[PDB]
Image (cartoon, rainbow, N blue to C red):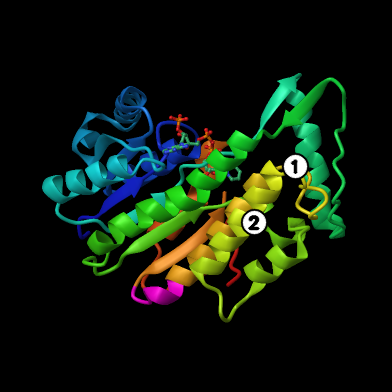
Amino acid sequence: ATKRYAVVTGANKGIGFEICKQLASKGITVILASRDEKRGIEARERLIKELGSEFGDYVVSQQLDVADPASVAALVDFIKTKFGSLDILVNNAGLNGTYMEGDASVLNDYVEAEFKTFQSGAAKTEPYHPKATGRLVETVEHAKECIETNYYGSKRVTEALIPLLQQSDSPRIVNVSSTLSSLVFQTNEWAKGVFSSEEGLTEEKLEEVLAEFLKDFIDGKQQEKQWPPHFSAYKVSKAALNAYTRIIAKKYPSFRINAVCPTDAEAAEAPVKLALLPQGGPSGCFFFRDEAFC
Ligand SMILES: NC(=O)c1ccc[n+]([C@@H]2O[C@H](COP(=O)([O-])OP(=O)(O)OC[C@H]3O[C@@H](n4cnc5c(N)ncnc54)[C@H](OP(=O)(O)O)[C@@H]3O)[C@@H](O)[C@H]2O)c1
């Protein structure tokens, strides 16, 4: 009943777009944030054409690059002067840190090899490329961008909007993570120990793991130092984001702060449920689709 305002980052396509659609259809007023201003304007138009023109006031486009402090600051100013309030943040903007050379479909072979680790717990530490048809390339610069967006980007946006969210009588933060965030994939025993800590976990320790991974990745010692052979930056960054989610869950008990592994419309249901979570919902948990954990 009570009017709510939500930010969804990286929301011009993919699951973000579907999160926005589903919040707007429930009466939430949504800020559709996109790295490029014109694609977000265009995404809003399609969103309004699909829901109906009566939703035109419930969706607003705003440029947002989570890696750019000035972009973040401009978004806080926009929300301040247009609405005055914020209730929901969905951190959906994200990068893989990888691309395909050659046949792009070999990616399904790489994703398959990772997913068997769930059925076996045997976390391979040696790089295995399933075919010579394609290759999953992970450059040093893409590893930096991936950490800078997934960890520091999400954290930058969260801390800029917390002051606004804290004036909500039910503030909600949802961090879109990945199954590759699971510690079964964290080959590096030091880093796994940090991520596993329930006591004495600090943002400082998380950032030390990130810097250590980036130093060994630059130095070319990814396998020497027992870092994951594939999706390496992605795994470390999304695990850090999970751990960071628990840290701020404990800092702000009056908030509900959660991570969630997510067709796109179906995958948006899980973050959407967490964005409208009741007062007694959990906080500090990583959810797989629609199932509890904490
Ligand atoms: N593929 C899956 O089914 C799957 C599975 C598990 C987890 N996820 C997670 O779910 C989220 C949604 O991704 P997706 O699968 O829908 O992929 P996607 O289509 O590539 O969407 C990612 C979105 O993030 C935006 N983005 C990236 N870097 C940004 C930055 N610097 N600042 C602001 N926006 C930025 C992109 O904007 P541009 O269009 O301007 O590039 C894009 O709209 C991600 O966080 C991803 O890690 C996805």
- In the rendered image, the residue lying farthest to the front is 219
Residue under pointer 2: 212
Q: Is residue 51 magenta?
A: no
Relative to residue 249, is residue 286 drawn left or right?
A: right
Location of residue 182 by image quarter: bottom right
Q: Residues within 10 Å of mark 2 (few under 14, many from 20)?
A: some
- The residue that label 1 is drawn on is 220
Mark 2 and mark 1 in contact? Answer it, CB < 8 Å. no
Mark 1 lies on a secondary structure that is: loop
Query: Percent from the top left, x then y, of residue 243?
Result: 56, 65
Residue 252 in magenta? yes
Question: Three-letter amino acid code at disc 1?
Answer: Gly
- For this rendering, which residue is in front, 39 or 102? 102
Tell me the amino acid under the disc marked 2.
Answer: Glu
**Could you give the CA–CA distance between mark 2 and mark 1, rounded to whole angstroms?**
12 Å
Percent x, y for residue 251?
A: 40, 75
Picture quadrant of residue 128: top right
Range shown magenta? 249-254
Q: Residue at x 34, y 59 (%)?
A: 159
Asked whether mark 1 lies closer than 8 Å to ligand 1, one says: no
Q: Secondary structure at mark 2?
A: helix
Quadrant in which the C terminus appears: bottom right
Nearest the viewer among 225 and 145 is 225
